[PDB]
């Protein structure tokens, strides 16, 4: 089944990880045009998520994921759930979000005490931690990049991301795992290196969003190897 993805940037590209994780699977995307990775930014596009779900349905999507973590968690857990229900009611399709994806990935891996490694500014990190606590997880600490640019996220390099994860875990080495939050980041090369060095799993926004969307679509598809414990 074709999987549809609502993505933050105006360009509306399928996130790059899809072709690496699931080379044989069909994805399509629709772009919100988020202006900044901030609550003010989210407010300016959040009301269009339903319209974009419908746009994807009209292009043949069989399931829809809102592929933005912060767009889906910034208002708390009930809003993530309610927005999902609205997308489902509007489209008659199975729907999900990237916040649900990371929650499901952390749960699947048995992660309860979770170190946060994020691209975001602290107001957004506080909202992430509150969302996770609402959902019965225990954030242990946070290290972040403080970036508000949307398209800027793709240019953060692997070494920076590996270091970010290692520093977040260093602060709380009792953590069961690491949440690497921001679906605009290119994290696939960082993940196995972090897992190798630290011996705990990483749940990363974009890869988790794919893993979750592929689960929702129901084919049983298996990802290519080398992308982290979440994928086997």
Image (tube, grey):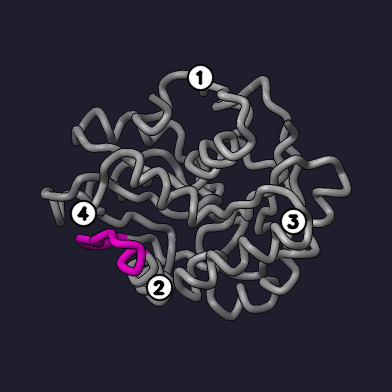
Q: Which residue is mark 2?
A: 127
Q: Which residue is mark 4?
A: 113
Q: Secondary structure at mark 4?
A: strand
Lower sequence index among marks 3 and 1: 3
Image quarter for residue 123?
bottom left
Q: What crowding class fits label 1: few (fewer than 14 Cα within 10 Å), some (14-19), or many (20 or more)?
A: few
Q: Which residues are magenta?
A: 132-143
**Which dot marks residue 31?**
3
Image quarter for residue 40?
bottom right
Q: Nearer the viewer, residue 194 or 221?
A: 221
51 is higher (above) or lower (below) than 66: below
- Circles 4 and 3: CB distance less than 8 Å? no
Lower sequence index among marks 3 and 2: 3
Q: Which residue is mark 1?
A: 224
Q: Alpha carbon of mark 3 to alpha carbon of mark 2: how far?
A: 23 Å
Residue at image x 60%, y 61%? 150
State which mark lies toward you, 4 or 2: 4
Q: Alpha carbon of mark 4 to alpha carbon of mark 2: how far?
A: 17 Å
Q: Alpha carbon of mark 2 to alpha carbon of mark 1: how far?
A: 33 Å
Point out residue 67 in the picture as x, y percentages from the top left corner: 60, 52
Lower sequence index among marks 1 and 4: 4
Q: Alpha carbon of mark 3 to alpha carbon of mark 1: how far?
A: 27 Å
Q: What crowding class fits label 3: few (fewer than 14 Cα within 10 Å), some (14-19), or many (20 or more)?
A: some
């Amino acid at each position: 089944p074709t999987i549809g993805m609502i993505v933050p940037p105006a360009a509306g590209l399928v996130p790059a990880d899809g072709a690496r994780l699931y080379p044989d699977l069909p994805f399509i995307a629709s772009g919100l045009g988020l202006g900044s990775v901030t609550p003010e930014g989210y407010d300016a596009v959040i009301e269009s998520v339903v319209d974009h779900a419908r746009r994807l349905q009209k292009q043949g999507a069989a399931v829809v994921s809102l592929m933005g973590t912060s767009l889906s968690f910034y208002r708390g857990a009930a809003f993530n759930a309610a927005l999902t229900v609205a997308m489902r009611e509007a489209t008659g399709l199975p729907c999900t979000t990237m916040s649900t994806a990371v929650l499901n990935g952390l749960r699947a891996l048995g992660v309860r005490r979770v170190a946060l490694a994020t691209a975001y500014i602290d107001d957004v990190n506080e909202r992430l931690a509150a969302f996770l606590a609402e959902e019965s997880l225990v954030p242990t600490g946070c290290r972040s990049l403080g970036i508000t640019g949307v398209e800027a996220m793709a240019r953060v390099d692997t070494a920076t991301l590996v270091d970010l994860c290692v520093r977040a875990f260093e602060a709380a080495p009792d953590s069961d795992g690491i949440l690497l939050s921001c679906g605009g980041l290119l994290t696939l090369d960082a993940i196995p290196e972090v897992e190798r060095r630290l011996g705990v799993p990483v749940v990363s926004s974009s890869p988790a969003g794919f893993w979750d969307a592929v689960r929702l679509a129901g084919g049983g598809a298996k990802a290519r190897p080398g992308y982290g414990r979440l994928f086997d």
